[PDB]
Image (cartoon, grey):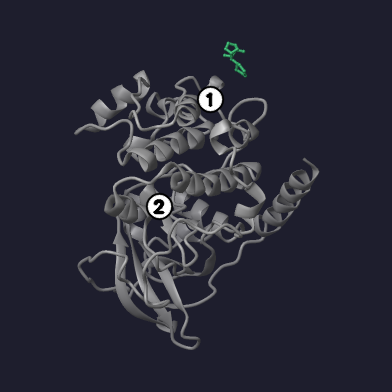
Amino acid sequence: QESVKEFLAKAKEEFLKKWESPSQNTAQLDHFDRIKTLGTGSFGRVMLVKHKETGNHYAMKILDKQKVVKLKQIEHTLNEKRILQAVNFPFLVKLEFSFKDNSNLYMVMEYVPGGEMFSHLRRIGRFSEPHARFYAAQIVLTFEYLHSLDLIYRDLKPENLLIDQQGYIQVTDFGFAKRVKGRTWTLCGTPEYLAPEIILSKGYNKAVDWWALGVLIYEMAAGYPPFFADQPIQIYEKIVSGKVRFPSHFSSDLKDLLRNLLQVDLTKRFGNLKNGVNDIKNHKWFATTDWIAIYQRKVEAPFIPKFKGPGDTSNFDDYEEEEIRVSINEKCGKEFTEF
Ligand SMILES: N[C@H]1[C@H](O)[C@@H](N2CCOCC2)[C@@H]2OC[C@H]1O2
């Protein structure tokens, strides 16, 4: 399809230019006012901030350099920043500024006020198949783009997908993404979404992102993921068996797609065969999908989140508010020279 070949050829040209010449130190902390904590992890936090000169709102990710080294995430945090300053796609969150100081690394992204897809899924119960299909088509197009750049994403799940002001998806949380020619080996991701070859400590490739799409479409349509248990070891046993049971309300076309995405043998899995992503785009479950209209954002979305303005935080949840302290001395300077 010529218009798709030329689109992706140009996409890769523009990605490589920025990849080979990354930007650095494009703002500083006292250019912003702090508003609220939006999310936390074992080495970082995300805060809503407002730029003092322009008044624009942003999601500022703050990573603690000393905890990054301890949790062994140095290369991952350098992957994340380099990838985010080089990509450009309608359904990816854009990096606007980055900088560092004596204690922390900072990535400043556009703020999306609609909240995480996870919150909306749990409030509604499950998404109808047309509603799940609209979100899934945006993930297929985003993976077609990323994989053509030799990037793997490695953390697809509903908590990492935001719903925007037009009801469309924005993928965020690029902390495990990596540029990969061939195979890679790091153990990372979230237990319920891991493909069997990751659990078995094998060299793996972009097929793990297509497995995770199968898990996501099942979770959107059922209300719960296909493999669950109280301990990760029990989750892993179910995954590598891959025996999966489908609710009776699933359509026959949906069950067929999911059996081909949740294929335990990676050499048989849709998205990893000779025809690549087109085995997915041409599947009967997507027969009603206008792929061009979705990319151009001309389709009316299933619902628009309720929010009052660009600074509204009502769709995110409440976290303890702690300080952003910067040490008087520099920490881990050498390890993050390239950030
Ligand atoms: N070639 C072998 C593969 O494991 C399968 N193929 C994967 C590539 O695409 C189509 C089918 C199928 O099962 C046995 C044989 O044919």
Which residue is drawn at the image coordinates 40% and 52% (left, top)? 160
- Say which element carries label 1: loop
Residue sitting farthest toward the right: 2
Residue 87 spot, x, y in % from top left: 61, 57
- Say which element carries label 2: helix
Q: Is residue 257 left or right of 194 when viewed as pictured?
A: right
Amino acid on which disc 2 is placed = Asn
Q: Residues within 10 Å of mark 2 (few under 14, many from 20)?
A: some
Residue 1 spot, x, y in % from top left: 77, 40
Residue 136 spot, x, y in % from top left: 50, 44
**Ligand 1's quadrant:** top right
| Distance (Cα) linking label 2 and label 1 | 24 Å
Q: Disc 1 designates what residue?
A: 269
Q: Disc 2 designates what residue?
A: 160
Q: Which of 73 and 173 is in front in this view?
A: 173
Q: How crowded is mark 1: few (under 14 residues within 10 Å), some or many (20 or more)?
A: many
Q: How many marks?
A: 2
Which residue is drawn at the image coordinates 45% and 34% (left, top)? 214
Examine the image and state in which quarter residue 151 appears. Answer: top right
